[PDB]
Structure formats: C-alpha cells, structure tokens
Image: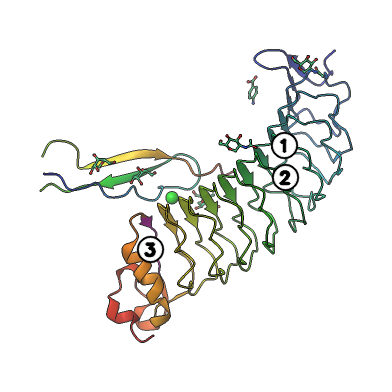
Amino acid sequence: SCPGACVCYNEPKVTTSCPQQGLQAVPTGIPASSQRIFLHGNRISHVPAASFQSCRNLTILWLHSNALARIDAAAFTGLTLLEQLDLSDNAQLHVVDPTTFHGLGHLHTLHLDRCGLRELGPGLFRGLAALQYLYLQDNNLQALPDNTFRDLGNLTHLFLHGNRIPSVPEHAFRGLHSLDRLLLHQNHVARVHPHAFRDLGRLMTLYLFANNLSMLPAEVLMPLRSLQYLRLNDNPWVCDCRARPLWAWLQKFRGSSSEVPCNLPQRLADRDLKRLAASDLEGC
Amino acid sequence: AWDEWSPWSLCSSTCGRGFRDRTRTCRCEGPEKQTKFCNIALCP
Ligand SMILES: *[C@@H]1O[C@@H](C)[C@@H](O)[C@@H](O[C@@H]2O[C@H](CO)[C@@H](O)[C@H](O)[C@H]2O)[C@@H]1O
Ligand SMILES: *[C@@H]1O[C@H](CO)[C@@H](O)[C@H](O)[C@H]1NC(C)=O
Ligand SMILES: *[C@@H]1O[C@H](CO)[C@@H](O)[C@H](O)[C@H]1NC(C)=O
Ligand SMILES: *[C@H]1O[C@H](CO)[C@@H](O)[C@H](O)[C@@H]1O
Ligand SMILES: *[C@H]1O[C@H](CO)[C@@H](O)[C@H](O)[C@@H]1O
Ligand SMILES: Nc1ccc(C(=O)O)cc1
Ligand SMILES: [Cl-]
C-alpha cells in the first residue's frame, strides 16, 4: 500500500513521508487518502500534470529542496483543500506558469523562496483569497508589477527581500488590506511611489534597508497608521532639505525605527537623520 | 511614579530567535527594562 521509499501512517493525519531518499520523481502509488505528503530533500526534477490528483483531501505538500526545473501548469489539479505548499529551495525552477495555483482556494501558506524566479507573471496569485504567508525572498525578481497581489486580502506576511526590485509602483501592493509584515530589504529599490502603501493601513513591520533610496516622498509613509517597526538603514540617504518630510515623520513616529544614516552632504555623513536638528533640513 | 514604557525595540536578529526590549524611567515598584521574544524569519 505504501511506496517502498516512504513511511505511511494514519495519525494524526494520513501521511506519506519520503524525505531525502534520493528520489528523482514523485513516487508512484502514494495512497489516495494522504492528507500530508513530505517529499522534501529529494532530487525531483519535474512535477507533471495531476501528480497528486487522487489525493483529494491533501492539505500539506512539501516539495522543497529538490531539483525542480519544471512544474506543469496542472501539477496541483485535484488539491482543492491544499493549505500549505512548500516549493522553496529549487534554485533552477526559474519560472512558475501563471495558472499553476489557480483553484487552490484554501491555500494559506506558499513558499517560493530560493527558486531562481525571474518574474511574477500576470495572474500568478489570482483568486488566492485565503493566502496568509507568501515567501518570495532570495529569487531574481526585477520588477513588482501593479496588482500582483490584488486578490490577497488575507495576506499577513509578504517576504520579498534578496531580489533585484528597482522600484515600488503605485499599485504593487494594492489589495493587501491585512498585511502585517512587508520585507523589502536587500533589493535595488530606488524609489517608492507616493501612494504605494495606500492599502497598508494595518502594516506593523516594514523593512526597506539595504536598498538604493536617497529620499522618500512626503506621502509614502503617511498611510502606515499601525506601523510599529521600521528599518531604513543601509541606504544612500541625502540629508538636505529634501529629507525634511521624512525627518518630520520620524520625529512623530511612536514605534521603533532603525538609524537612518546620512550619506551626503559630507558634513553630515557621520549622522542619523532622526537625530538631526530641524535647522539642518531647512531650505525647501 | 513610573513613566510610560518605551515602544518595543526592533528585533535583535531578523533570522531565528531574537528579542526586543523596552525601558521606562522612574518619576516606584516594578522593573525598569523588559525583553520579549521575536522571530522574524527562518534563514538557511
Ligand atoms: C533580517 O531579515 C532576515 C529575513 C534576513 O534577510 C536577515 O539577513 C541575514 O542575517 C543573518 C544574521 O542574522 C546573516 O547571517 C545573513 O547573512 C543575512 O542574510 C536580515 O538581517
Ligand atoms: C477524503 O475524506 C473523506 C472524509 O473522511 C473520505 O470519505 C474520502 O474517502 C477521502 N478521500 C480520499 C481520496 O481518500
Ligand atoms: C480571510 O480571513 C478571515 C479571518 O482570518 C477568515 O474569517 C476568512 O475565512 C478568510 N477568507 C478565506 C479563507 O477565503
Ligand atoms: C507599559 O506597559 C503597559 C503597556 O504595555 C502599561 O502597564 C503601561 O503603559 C506601561 O507604561
Ligand atoms: C510592543 O509590543 C506590541 C507590538 O509588538 C505592542 O503592545 C506595542 O507596540 C509594544 O511597544
Ligand atoms: N517534519 C515532520 C514530520 C512528521 C510530522 C508529523 O507526523 O506530525 C510533522 C513534521
Ligand atoms: Cl523588527
């Protein structure tokens, strides 16, 4: 009944577990009653269409740390109750067909970090209304297109750090009304649209450190009425009068922020924007 | 005659187990500093 490379047990949930067994393919004969399937740490290179189709009650599927080079668009057909899908640490994946997650209406945790992803294609996260945690860090993303997350009204954690994102457009984060933590550090972000955070009134943690920011428009942080933790260090901040709105916002912020180190002008290059006097930012 | 607690700090680490702290100044029974657990992310 159980595949030779696996251990199968019924409690607490029906589980087929075969991690780190040197598998090059999804094993045949996984029990249709499986509720959890653990295939992490193998060398699986392809997930064909309907690889788990008979497992109608599946809620946990772990495929991380494999050698995935292709996931069929219909790989997850049948998995209408799937709640957790870990595809992370498959550095040669590179692309996920934008229909791959369609129909996963109970999905609440989706791991896609360390997958070599070059882009988030149109519709990739369509209709994932139950999604809570979305891990996209440590890929090769070079853009955050408008409306990429627009249906993710229940998302609370969005990790995007460790990519090559050069800017945040107006509607990148449209729809993210429940978002709690937004991790955007270690990117190439050179500007944030003034209204990029309009829907993030419930955000509590924002990381923007290790980017390419020299300034933030006056409006950017205004919508962040619940913010408690803010990291802005390791950016080339200019501390002249163009920094006055950020300075003023930081003076009134009731949470905790990182140092905001001045890069220029040289006479202030040894200072934290937060600690400057108002007279240092006069002029415009 | 305690003053209000400061906001909790940034997390000591953003990978794995870390802590935040907060402080308050007198004017008086109770602590002066507290810490609490934080975990932002798992890092390989
Ligand atoms: C805070 O956010 C995390 C999600 C990571 O991106 C952290 O970076 C990692 O920090 C550890 C030390 O805690 C370093 O050893 C890793 O090299 C670094 O990627 C970040 O500080
Ligand atoms: C799914 O669970 C239901 C309810 O326990 C059960 O009747 C059904 O046989 C299960 N489906 C599979 C494919 O095992
Ligand atoms: C969205 O989140 C709320 C609160 O957790 C929940 O009641 C609702 O069912 C969720 N929507 C889904 C799962 O589609
Ligand atoms: C700090 O702690 C609590 C609020 O967290 C209260 O006892 C009071 O605000 C104190 O200053
Ligand atoms: C720290 O703890 C929570 C947020 O993590 C709040 O009670 C408040 O922000 C406090 O300073
Ligand atoms: N890694 C895991 C292995 C097994 C189980 C379980 O049987 O609950 C959970 C996690
Ligand atoms: Cl933090």
CB contact under 8 Å: marks 1 and 2: yes
The residues bearing labels 1 and 2 have C-alpha atoms spaced at a distance of: 7 Å
The residue positioned 12% from the left and 36% from the top of the image is: B29
Which residue is tagged 3? A259
Give the mark, 3 or 2, whose residue is nearer the N terminus: 2
Q: Residue A27 lies in magenta, yes or no? A: no
Residue A122: name its quadrant: bottom right
Which residue is tagged 2? A127
Give the mark, 3 or 1, whose residue is nearer the N terminus: 1
Ligand 3 within 8 Å of disc 2? The answer is no
* Residue A214 visible in the snapshot: yes
Question: Disc number at residue A105?
Answer: 1
Indicate the quadrant containing the N terminus of chain A: top left, top right, bottom left or bottom right: top right
Question: Disc number at residue A75?
Answer: none
* Residue A272 visible in the snapshot: no
Using the image, determine if residue A173 lies above or below residue B38.
below
**Which percent across, then down, holds residue B37?**
39, 38
Chain letter of the residue beneath label 1 in the structure image: A
- Which residues fall within the magenta stretch? A256-261
